[PDB]
Image: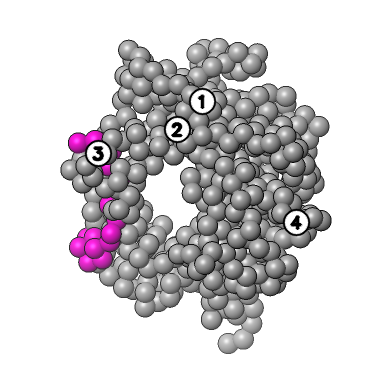
Amino acid sequence: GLIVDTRDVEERVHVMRETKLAPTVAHGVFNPEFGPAALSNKDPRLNEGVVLDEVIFSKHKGDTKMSAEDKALFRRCAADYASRLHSVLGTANAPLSIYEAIKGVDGLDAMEPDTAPGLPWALQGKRRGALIDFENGTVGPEVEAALKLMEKREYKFACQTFLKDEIRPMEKVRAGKTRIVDVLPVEHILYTRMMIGRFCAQMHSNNGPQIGSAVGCNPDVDWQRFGTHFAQYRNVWDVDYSAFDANHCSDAMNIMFEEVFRTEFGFHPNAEWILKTLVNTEHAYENKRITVEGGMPSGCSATSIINTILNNIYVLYALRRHYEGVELDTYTMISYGDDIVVASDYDLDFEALKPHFKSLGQTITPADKSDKGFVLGHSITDVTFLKRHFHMDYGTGFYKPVMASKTLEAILSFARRGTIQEKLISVAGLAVHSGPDEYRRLFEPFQGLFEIPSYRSLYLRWVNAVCGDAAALEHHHH
Ligand SMILES: [Mn+2]
């Protein structure tokens, strides 16, 4: 994004906090090169010269204005992807009711009752529950008023910069690279869900290579589906971006919103409008108000879907900008936000695509260090996706999502107080695919103090999850 204005105002929107994460018993055993992100400039771990807001907004180094020709190409790619998307999902894209937007529907989680309400409510000491009845799925007069402004396209708002309390590599922690959540007003999230939540629900339910989206997938179940699909192709590329969300140019965002969320695909006219309010945004950090043109705000509602859609269009765009005769069946891919796996039988020169991604303001690099850039010949078993490898389970012959042990060690080394038992059961679901020896080793520090699921129990759970028929078939003989 391009920072076009910065000004100081009277109202100080607080951003500095103390971490809720503490080391666990596993920290002393694994000693990970990971720690809680700095949530304050006074944090002693920070390097000299580090000012949080400067580092946080340093990713905004311009809004790439695409040529007329490139925008035309982009719109064709956006429309072609949209065509695939709405062919698979259908056109049942009318607004959710206020009740449905709050309470959720099949394939769309309910709204969080006690997360940050955003501005100006945070400054007024009003929590989300003061504005919305999450039990009954109704809204108070303030939100009702705001919804009318959105209906009339007169609604304006500021985003609240919220520091992400999370574990990061210590290199990034000390550099002040604390990630953020751009907290939009609760009514904006509500209306966005009203406008495109039905579409988002359908995206989740139809996740896969066909629509190029893994959003709403269950890695336990879907690694078999994804792994088997990508194993059929000669080439598989693990592509990485740098600041994917920040570098979405306004042209790309606008054109995507225009082609994907058209009224002819069942959307209300304000679906495009409310999405377009994400393009030029004002961000509150303490007394500073920073206006950014371009880039996707780091939200938690429709952000992953939007980023996933753009990722799909980018690949089509880049390939078509370099090669002639490129269509959606020239390659295959799946994406979750910035994360992406691409495959094709064609020897696609991904190194040569670099400048074409650059015309979108995006910088692509291979997942591995840089073996003289991108290369052909890699398979599904070489790549990572959602921090998970595609490994073959010897017991079943199904693909399983295997996380690196150092990742799991880092995850296990920290936790929010009072949540550890819950976290361990969750992480056990991730760790089971590493095998019984590694599973045992990872949870050994917690044995006795907490209930650790048996490897056996999680393996059997997984077998049925990935293939119920296989689980059944194993009981045919004594
Ligand atoms: Mn990657």
Q: Is residue 367 left or right of residue 349?
A: left
Classify mark 2: residues with Cα within 10 Å, few (<14), some (14-19) or many (20+). many
Which residue carries the number 3 mark? Answer: 49
Which residue carries the number 4 mark? Answer: 323
Classify mark 3: residues with Cα within 10 Å, few (<14), some (14-19) or many (20+). few
Q: CA distance from mark 1 to mark 4?
A: 35 Å
Q: In the rendered structure, which amino acid carries the disc numbered 3?
A: Gly
Q: In the rendered structure, which amino acid carries the disc numbered 1?
A: Thr
Label 1 residue SS: strand
- Residue at (69% x, 36% y) in the render: 67
Is residue 477 placed above or below 428 in the rendered structure?
below
Q: CA distance from mark 3 to mark 4?
A: 45 Å
Residue 281 circle label? 1
Which residue carries the number 2 mark? Answer: 182
Would you say the residues marked 1 and 2 are in contact, meaning their CB atoms lie under 8 Å apart? yes
Specify whether residue 355 is in view: yes
Mark toward the start of the polypeptide (1 vs 4): 1
Pinpoint residue 173: horizontal percent, then vertical percent: 29, 48
- Magenta range is 25-42
Where residue 37 sits, quadrant-wise, is top left
